[PDB]
Image (spheres, coloured by chain):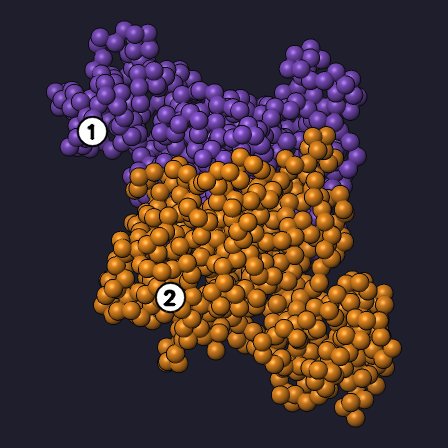
Chain colours: A orange, B purple
Amino acid sequence: YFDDSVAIVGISCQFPGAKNHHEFWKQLREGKESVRFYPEDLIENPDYVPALSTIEGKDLFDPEFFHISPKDAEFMDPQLRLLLLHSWKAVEDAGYVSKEIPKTSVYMSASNNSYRSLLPEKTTPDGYVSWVLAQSGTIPTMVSHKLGLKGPSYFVHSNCSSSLVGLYSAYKSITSGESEYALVGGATLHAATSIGYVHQNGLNFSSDGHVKAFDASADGMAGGEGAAVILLKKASQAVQDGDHIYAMLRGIGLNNDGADKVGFYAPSVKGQTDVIQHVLDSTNIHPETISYIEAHGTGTTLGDPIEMSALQQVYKRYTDREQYCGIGSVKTNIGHLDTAAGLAGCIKVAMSLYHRELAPTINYTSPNPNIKFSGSPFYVADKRKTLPERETPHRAALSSFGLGGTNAHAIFEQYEDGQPPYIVPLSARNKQRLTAYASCLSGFLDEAENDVSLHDLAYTYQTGREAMEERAVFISHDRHDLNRQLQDFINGNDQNILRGEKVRSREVSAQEMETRDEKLKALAALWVEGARVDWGLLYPDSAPQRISAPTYPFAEERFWP
Amino acid sequence: YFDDSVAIVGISCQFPGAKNHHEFWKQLREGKESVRFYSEEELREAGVPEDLIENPDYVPALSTIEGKDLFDPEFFHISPKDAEFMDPQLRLLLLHSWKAVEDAGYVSKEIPKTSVYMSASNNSYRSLLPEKTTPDGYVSWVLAQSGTIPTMVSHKLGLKGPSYFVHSNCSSSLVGLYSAYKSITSGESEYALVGGATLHAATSIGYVHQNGLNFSSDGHVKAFDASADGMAGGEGAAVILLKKASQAVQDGDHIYAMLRGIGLNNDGADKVGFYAPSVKGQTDVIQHVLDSTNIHPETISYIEAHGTGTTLGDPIEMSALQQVYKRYTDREQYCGIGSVKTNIGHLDTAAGLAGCIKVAMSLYHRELAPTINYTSPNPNIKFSGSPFYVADKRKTLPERETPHRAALSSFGLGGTNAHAIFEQYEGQPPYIVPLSARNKQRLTAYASCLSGFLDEAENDVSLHDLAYTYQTGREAMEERAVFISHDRHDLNRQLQDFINGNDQNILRGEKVRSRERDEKLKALAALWVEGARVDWGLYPDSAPQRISAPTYPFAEERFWP
């Protein structure tokens, strides 16, 4: 059933308002808009829109982790830096040690932000190195080189639809057997902080800084900045391996509008129609089984009606059922993230399916009077909605239509205990980082909305994280005790915690192999001194499951010209 | 047989020394180096700093094309203001895309099922624009985004296949070629355009040779030679058109060569550093391409190497080829090795296409062109007793039963490797040549190009095929002239009359608007010059063939900040 499917097994993102994807999903469920509203000419201009949707810490990085010099880190634009960080995290989110999954392709997209222009005129050996680090192919290749990945690795771009070209490239590589996994990343991070813009005739930008998708009041888009990477995997293999799967990608297609439209910057109903139709034909998925569509959904006066006209024209070929499929756009929450737009949409879809719930689209009061929702398949999904139990898995589609005419549509599908004590091995590159890890893990235990399985959590840190030089092991019976020990560690009250410094890895010996509580303590002590223990020994008759958990706590050092 | 093959049917290039691919092949066959070296005089004019001139390590070399700044925006209905916002890579790849389709004998709007893949450098062109400029800020930003290149091509040519930018540093063109191969062999598109261009946004004569750059001590690329001590750059642009192989054959296209298979990988972590080469990565990609094609290495007559002339890279390249081919054969000295970088330098994103075009034209002309700057083998490489010889002479490819095959390698900085295998593929007067262009000045230029071609062609030119190419392989435009001729010398005389203003004997049309045996020919001609869409299907009992012929003579207007 899953031969033509790919599993989404890891996510890492950093979007306006949200430091990670779990916080992102929370903010989407709650209807939160993360656009922020606040030089004399501009201040006084009645058409200046005082709005910015960005992430923080574009300048922060941990070059030492990757053996990058401080000088070279400064030569690196923020998109390169954050896509590397997020690639590392996406694999850890999935519960894999990157160097243990070499059969992984890498596809990345980012903006031309002119970062290298910021460097000193004299600078621009430095001239050549900084030029190389500015070339777009350096992004995915740097990921491959630093993570240990050997599949095809390259940059892809189609303006707004870029993320979806990344996703298409992953789909193709994995379904063909070229690779087992793929990383897909997108980031549009400007090399300046420029608050607001001036609303004017020659531009289809919102009059008030809000994206009002599908609304009567929709008068233009607004941009936002962020970074995201996801890890995909051959579906049958993910199921076999017991991975934590957010959702399945069942198919995806691309086209270009060509000449058949009035102008280079215009939208095209015909191009949208045809790519939707192409994806229905390749997947053979019937439009009656789609419960939700994450639209391109930019909130332009001409684009929103065009988008719905294309969907209605195609679905009419298949059905007359009414009001069964919701429509929304994450651009309402965080703006149009350019190269990352398609991945913001994808991550919304995947989390909706994972949580069996739709999140609302926002800034909506009344339907655009040019759009006829009534009596069509579609309603505007302006509330939370539980996805009902039913026999067919729920499916959700996603659109992204780029400036220049390259269109993409994709269809996704929903996919659906030990005994204490539990051993949580943490490690990082140095003591400061390790302490930060404990602090991350503690915050996670406190902030998680639901109870957290220590069986699964421990197994994730055992088998899903690279063992580094600074080590600590926490043996605990329950979450509150584990948190107490983490807080003791954070505070320097270290006395009863197994610790290792400058640890060097080694193969277990025959001698080392020569009660269950005693044995657990012993494995832990071997690991903290560097022995590559077989954590499988903990689980003769339990079956832990890798879960989404805090990922490496990178240093936050500033590099900027 | 050809199910897994793609035909190369059109080429357009502009490389150091060569204004087109025919001149390029001539120059290769003759062993010409097109790197320019500057005297002290020459450096002073062109105004290079006397402190560079006096530096004993300054290398006074440049391998570039001319006229990076020249474009014809009116042809594409681009405003002069927007033309200035366009970087030269975007401009030249558009021009060369138009030309490649004409080189193939197709009217671009008649081949909508065409994918588009482009690669180019980050040259910081937008940074050159005024600060006030940077609606202009947004439009120039859009035009600076990499996805605009292929999508501008799709839009302006009328193409509706997937369209996007790809990049993997020096191997980029081969990622483009791979994407074309996959799109066509899967049935996604019938055709594809593949382009590459690295054009810097400055003219910077020479460089300073120094430790910690792997750049030639004297500006020559000395591939495989004992004196090889580093690479040297060049700039250029190229686009080719590929087509489903069986359909190219069925349509009677002019086929330069077939592409039989191609593959990609990344070196990953298994090497000492980001910027280093990798014998393992190369070995593995070559092996992958042999296994996917099932082509035996004894049938390969020539390899166009990545061939950069670095002290460590050249031996690594041969070690990988030797290690793979050893597993198949003990035969000796049957396969040549060479590198076009010896002629024109390392063309970065266009390096792979320069190699492809050399291979294609070698196969088409059944001859190998020499690799240059080669006296004596690198003593770390053992050619003796291996399959390989350095192809430092012209060589005729003998008649044999198995078609000749030639492979191509491109190994990017950041570790994305590509390898491809290519294979050789083998009416009565008067004639009517209907020429048309956008205005009278372009039409005159067209006549002049056509006349020059007739004079410069090394062999006799079939008027039967030439006329058919202009009839059926060129968009009929508003300024029209028809030349009815019995032979090449008369045709040339009429073209020269036209060029000189003596056009009273030539049927002409101005501001023509399209609308729905000797006697009959004259009648078609008069209809066509007034805009009637005549059926050139003149050919009840002859079968003309489309050929490579002069393409649209774009205006050469300067746009530069």
Q: Name the residue located 49 percent from the left edge and 72 percent from the top edge.
A: A354
For the image, the number of numbered tags is 2
- Above or below, A176 against B224 in this view is below
Estimate the x, y position of residue A535 in percent, counting from the top left. 72, 79
Output the chain of dot 2.
A
Kindly report the distance in space between the C-alpha atoms of the residues bearing marks 1 and 2: 49 Å
Q: Nearer the viewer, mark 1 or mark 2?
A: 2
Q: Amino acid at mark 1?
A: Ser
Give the position of the N terminus of chain A as an image quadrant.
bottom left
User: Which element type, helix, strand or loop, lies under badge 2?
Assistant: loop
Residue B313 screen position, x and y as percent: 70, 42
Quick check: A496 left or right of A298?
Answer: right
Indicate the position of residue A501 as horizontal and vertical percent values. 85, 68
Horizontally, residue A137 falls left or right of residue A511, namely: left
Count residues near mark 1 (Cα–Cα under 10 Å), then give few for <14, some for 14-19, many for 20+. Answer: some
Quadrant of the image occupied by residue A371: bottom left
Residue A190 in the image: above or below residue B202: below
Residue located beneath label 1 in the image: B514
- Decide which of A458, A100 is in the foreground and name it: A458
The chain containing the residue under callout 1 comes to: B
Which residue in the rendered view is the most extreme toward the left? Answer: B519
